[PDB]
Image 1 (cartoon, rainbow, N blue to C red):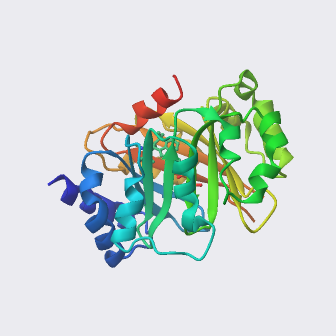
Image 2 (image 1 turned 30 degrees about the vertical axis):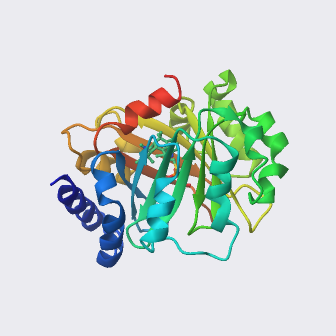
Amino acid sequence: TIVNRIRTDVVNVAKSFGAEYSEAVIDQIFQGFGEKFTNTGFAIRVQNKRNQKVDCNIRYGEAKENCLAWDIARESGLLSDQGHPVDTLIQEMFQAIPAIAYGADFDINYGLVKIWHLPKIVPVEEAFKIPSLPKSVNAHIDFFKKYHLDALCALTVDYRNKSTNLYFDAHHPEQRTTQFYKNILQSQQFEVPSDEVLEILVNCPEIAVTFNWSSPGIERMCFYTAFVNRETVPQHINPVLKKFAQEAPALLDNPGFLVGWSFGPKKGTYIKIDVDYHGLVVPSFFHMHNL
Ligand SMILES: [C-]#[N+][C@@H]1[C@H]2c3c[nH]c4cccc(c34)C(C)(C)[C@H]2C[C@@H](Cl)[C@]1(C)C=C
Ligand SMILES: CC(C)=CCSP(=O)(O)OP(=O)(O)O
């Protein structure tokens, strides 16, 4: 079956990258969501957030107007009340902005970590009405204006990290210059990467900005780029990129990949790479950003 091949592949990725994982967690996740993994946008992700440690996430998305993952996770025990503003945030999101899709994200050592809300691209003003957003979001209106973060293409609630992301379509001509990325990164006193990475960033069609309830500032920013096959991933930039690009499983032989470049302060400066397991994610990425 597809679901058994997926579960096998996930375990094999975790063992190959030495990622911490829990067989009991994986059993819970697949009990609730394995059927969903078989026939929707499904990806396996690895990242090097923590020092000398690779983490493995699995995630899916589908074009439903309601947030089915929330009901499944509540019923299957994968999401309990946190005693925290995240408890109702996703509900508020789907009440405040109409969704064309939703998604969910799982750390295979923990369980459900995030749920995504995917609207049609809307002005970012539509998010300022969401009551339980961290106050730092409204406090950053002038920042969003200045860096042409006006076109909101997704929202996410990170239940484990207790944080939220806003995702923007990087449509503005200024975002085709390396100076834009140097300036938005320096504005947060984040690390500025090499010129190589900068000329990769200028092609990023999407920018994520992370907020939380523990600071007035931005926690980290992420620039996302897709690659149509293993060969065009910039494997030389980092060993995790090379190893995952050459080894990641998929249902076709040469799958595409989504690469996120994260930047923070002792920070979240790191790489994320996801494999387009079924082949739907990468085209939907280009389509949602009109490329
Ligand atoms: C299918 N789908 C999902 C989609 C998604 C959820 N949140 C997003 C925020 C920005 C962009 C995207 C998403 C897409 C459309 C590029 C997409 C990515 C893949 Cl990796 C995911 C997570 C499924 C495994
Ligand atoms: C397009 C990408 C692959 C999904 C967007 S959500 P994310 O996984 O990048 O969010 P975080 O890394 O948890 O901040």
